[PDB]
Length: 99
Length: 8
Length: 274
Picture 1 (cartoon, each protein chain N blue to C red):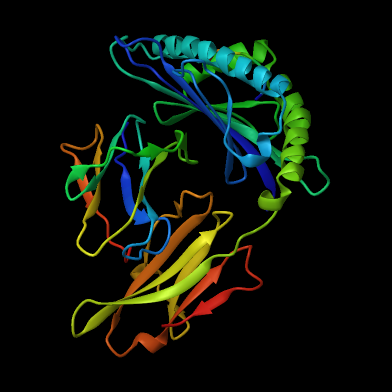
Picture 2 (tube, rainbow over the protein chains, first blue to last red; picture 1 turned 120 degrees about the vertical axis):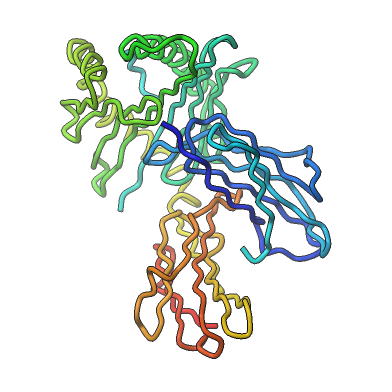
């Protein structure tokens, strides 16, 4: 009885190089609720990351938002790394400012 | 919150 | 539609690592306003929206106590469920509850809710008449019998028809400046060439509230449903929401596509072009 997380990586405001912003990783549609989520900068885990309070949708699947303050640049690469009982290995999703 | 207490 | 309040409870067992953790969040429509976490050092119901901060210590003490009681009750329930399903004490299990009210234009209850899920599956729910239960399986029928005998449905009906909508009306007035204000989406279309032959048109809806929205692409006035990528509506992190829809179009055909946006915050439905 297990559902694998959907993952979206995106910024709170339209991305602009050199402008302060927030980097989001939204995980949803998963069950059970235990889940490991990391935000990465150039492949390295970001330390100051906060997340929303555990809640769930009409179909009972859980969702959480993980977020951190960041200032995007041209070359810096960001991603979200997710692990869940339904995953054989951590899933990595890269931040694309066009998505 | 509802103050009604009943275990399943 | 109608304004609503909802509480969402989640208890998760963790055998060998202590007692089940209880978490509660409360929402008014799409705005979270309180939270409780049983693992906290001094477990307290805590504010999560500006308009609830004004509530006095009696409010916070009472609700904190109810959450503490609910923590213990859920632990009993989890133990009980394990017995019903003949499960061992080795595995982790989940109990979820959602309940709340929808208020009508007259200020009375439009519809009440109170349903449970065990391990992600419907377990038992209070029917719309607020006087009977729908039990998913034989285990839930044991619970039903207990709750019938304990007259649980009546107690919940009283809460839903009175207390619930009363406090909902209170929250709606105290937070009217945000809760009863619909923020329309800021919208635009972006263009992303894939090759010499095609390109992606993406229609954006940003910073809107409430979350309910409709985004559609049309070509020559015809729906492109089965050809559109629609991402799930997502939180911006500032209490507003985001969504986009995308279609792949032949180069030179961009002008034939229109994006359509419906949201209760808009004066009227929008039509967008690249």
